[PDB]
Image (cartoon, coloured by chain):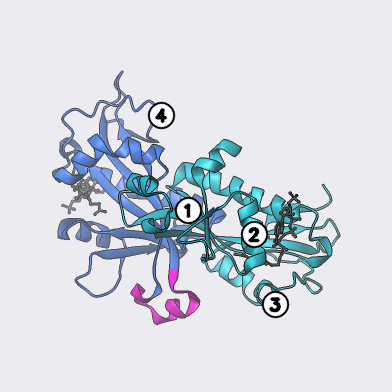
Chain colours: A blue, B cyan
Amino acid sequence: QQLTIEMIADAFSYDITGFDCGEEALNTFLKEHLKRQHDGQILRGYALVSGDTVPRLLGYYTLSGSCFERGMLPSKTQQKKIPYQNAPSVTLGRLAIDKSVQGQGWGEMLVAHVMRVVWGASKAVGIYGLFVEALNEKAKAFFLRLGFIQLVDENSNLLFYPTKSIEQLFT
Amino acid sequence: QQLTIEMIADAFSYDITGFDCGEEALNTFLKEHLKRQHDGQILRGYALVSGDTVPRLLGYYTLSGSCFERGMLPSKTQQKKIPYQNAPSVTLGRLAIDKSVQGQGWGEMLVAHVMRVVWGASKAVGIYGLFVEALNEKAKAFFLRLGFIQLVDENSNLLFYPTKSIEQLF
Ligand SMILES: CC(=O)SCCNC(=O)CCNC(=O)[C@H](O)C(C)(C)COP(=O)(O)OP(=O)(O)OC[C@H]1O[C@@H](n2cnc3c(N)ncnc32)[C@H](O)[C@@H]1OP(=O)(O)O
Ligand SMILES: CC(=O)SCCNC(=O)CCNC(=O)[C@H](O)C(C)(C)COP(=O)(O)OP(=O)(O)OC[C@H]1O[C@@H](n2cnc3c(N)ncnc32)[C@H](O)[C@@H]1OP(=O)(O)O
């Protein structure tokens, strides 16, 4: 499957009929809100797409600028380096892969693409890392295996991947 | 141009000894904290610099990713377009010009550069506009005069410039 990742095109001429990641909220979001919030500067959207005449959308993700409370950091050493109430961040608002193509590493590949975008962004604007709220335990284990660190307590869904680690990816 | 704007270089070999914008907190921050928070990915810093062998720094600013309460926006209609409690933003943490070159448009020129950077950033990551807390009434009038919007109430120092306005500039 020769799939490619792109920012969602202005025309949004994707074939999304039948898209189902197995979580209805993210299926509905793709259909109703992705493009409008992208054009409204609430998020920016990226799509994993096929090479058909009308490219089919097989996955997508969204990024928004954010910040989060310094106290959520597990390392009190890192906390002492943040001289303000909040640490700056980018939030992975949503990530979803279509059922037809799950379990092959496409989810992993989208996260790698996220990392490169956030890395580029971190050079121009202060971004201490990538923040994500795991939607459920299945998603949480997914992010933990990719190396995300746990914020707050051991049963919180708030995870974080530091820019310091992102830059190590692209040396 | 006589002075040029750049992201602060990794070596930070700028001559900052004589810098004085007239607010001691912003002078002290330049000297003690700017470069280390830039390297710490807390902010990214940009400087207005001369062309001497050791470049002299005549101004600087910092940008950090952020978000802010949707309720801050004055227009209840605009609030309905933001489907969450917080709107994504970039914060202008600091902006300062050395007194020797204040009143010549350099502050305005730095803000324009800010907007250009924020505009580029908004293409890749969702950013609803540029957030700033004015340090004092003098700074507040400066940003209002460049077209920033008053958030909360007429007596708050929280101001905002929407990406929608930035796009019209560019
Ligand atoms: C903010 C949020 O919470 S986003 C929430 C995430 N999204 C959702 O919950 C919606 C529904 N879920 C999904 O869309 C998907 O399940 C996702 C995005 C969470 C995971 O996407 P997937 O493509 O299934 O993940 P990915 O295939 O990268 O996971 C690795 C698995 O693929 C297998 N795999 C096969 N080939 C490869 C490869 N080349 N590289 C890596 N992994 C591979 C591994 O065996 C591994 O299996 P295991 O995890 O069962 O041990
Ligand atoms: C988050 C923060 O950093 S807010 C803190 C702001 N920084 C400071 O207070 C530090 C000390 N001050 C400074 O460094 C500078 O005085 C600044 C940044 C506030 C202003 O920069 P300057 O270079 O002096 O301003 P510049 O000459 O570019 O002014 C451009 C325009 O703004 C206007 N302006 C500037 N200050 C004011 C003011 N206090 N009231 C009204 N208008 C003003 C000017 O009149 C000019 O408009 P015009 O061209 O139509 O006449």
Residue A159 percent across, percent down from the top left: 30, 64
Tell whether position B57 is magenta: no
Q: Quadrant of ligand 2?
A: bottom right
Instruction: Tell me whether circle 1 and circle 2 mark residues in contact (CB < 8 Å).
Output: no
Tell me which segment is drawn in magenta.
A71-86
Which chain contains the residue that carries disc 4? Answer: A
Nearer to me, B14 or B90: B90
Which chain contains the residue that carries disc 3? Answer: B
The amino acid on which the numbered mark 3 sits, given as a three-letter code, is Glu
A108, above or below B157, in the image: above
Which chain contains the residue that carries disc 2? Answer: B
Q: How many marks?
A: 4
Q: Residue at x 29, y 40 (%)?
A: A60
Instruction: Tell me whether circle 4 and circle 3 mark residues in contact (CB < 8 Å).
Output: no
Residue A13 is drawn in which quadrant?
top left
Tell whether B68 sits left or right of B35.
left
The residue carrying mark 4 is A10
The 10 Å Cα crowd at callout 1, few under 14, some 14 to 19, many 20 or more, is many
The residue carrying mark 2 is B141
Quadrant in which the C terminus of chain B appears: top right
Q: Which disc, if any, is residue A119? A: 1
Instruction: Tell me whether circle 4 and circle 1 mark residues in contact (CB < 8 Å).
Output: no
The residue carrying mark 3 is B24
Disc 2 secondary structure class = helix
The 10 Å Cα crowd at callout 2, few under 14, some 14 to 19, many 20 or more, is some
